[PDB]
Amino acid sequence: QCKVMCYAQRHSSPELLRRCLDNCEK
Amino acid sequence: IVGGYTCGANTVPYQVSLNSGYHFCGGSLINSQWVVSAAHCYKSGIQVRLGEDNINVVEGNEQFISASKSIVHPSYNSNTLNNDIMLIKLKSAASLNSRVASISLPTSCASAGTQCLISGWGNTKSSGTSYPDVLKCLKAPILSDSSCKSAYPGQITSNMFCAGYLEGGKDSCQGDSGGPVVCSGKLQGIVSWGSGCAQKNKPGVYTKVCNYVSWIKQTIASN
Ligand SMILES: [Ca+2]
């Protein structure tokens, strides 16, 4: 559940979130 | 922090804001040169903001100091968030003759039921988003292993614990990561993750700091 855990993280950086979600596809 | 209250300026003097274009994570000062945070908060160009209360208005007691090093735990697993801990070294020592002070490391791991203070500038809404100007606080108990594992089947390692309320309503949230869970004056947790925020049967999951005391002390000594 890669994308799910990217959203589970409790930071508030859009850049870190978008990086996490993109990396789930790679 | 959802369901919390305004702490009041510098009532949580070891709390820091990590700022890299904006506030994005918290951290805890553990001595004049070192801050503990979450590994998933790693990124370039971190400035540490100590003595902060209102993140948008300089008004006294703030110290803004660039990070010089960010050392992520060598076993951090970004897929599972196991070992979600990072140490940040400040480019210059903070001044503690001040409102700012450090938080002690634990001498043992805390027990279920123990009430802790969780704090941060993260989202204050249980759905939707609203980031506060001033630091928020929440008192929350450590939950039992079994209730934690029941809420997060297959996902809780020995380096994590849950704190909060199975009825929901009160929890940490996005923007709080890396910040403190302090229980009787000891740093026991680092805000790490959860399913949503303040949801039923979905308490916050926190890095279990008592497992890392020797790694922390050795890292500080060698860097
Ligand atoms: Ca300020």
Image (spheres, coloured by chain):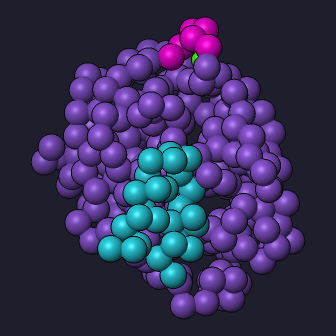
Relative horizontal placement of residue B205, taking residue B82 as reference (left or right) = right
Relative horizontal placement of residue B15, taking residue B221 as reference (left or right) = right
Residue interval drawn in magenta: B57-62
- Taking the spot 50% from the left edge, 46% from the top edge, the residue there is A13
The C terminus of chain B sits in image quarter: top left
Q: Position of residue B43 (x, y in %)?
A: 33, 46
- Taking the spot 74% from the left edge, 46% from the top edge, the residue there is B129
Q: Judge by depth and name the residue closer to the eye, A25 or B171.
A: A25
**Residue A14 in sight from this viewpoint:** yes
Where on the image, by quarter, is ligand 1?
A: top right
Main structural element of the magenta stretch: helix, strand or loop?
loop
Q: Position of residue B207 (x, y in %)?
A: 48, 65
**Display colour for chain A:** cyan
Against B55, residue B112 (above or below) is below
Relative horizontal placement of residue A12, taking residue B166 as reference (left or right) = left
Q: Position of residue B183 (x, y in %)?
A: 62, 54
The chain displayed purple equals B
Q: Judge by depth and name the residue closer to the eye, B130 or B67.
A: B130
Against B147, residue B57 (above or below) is above
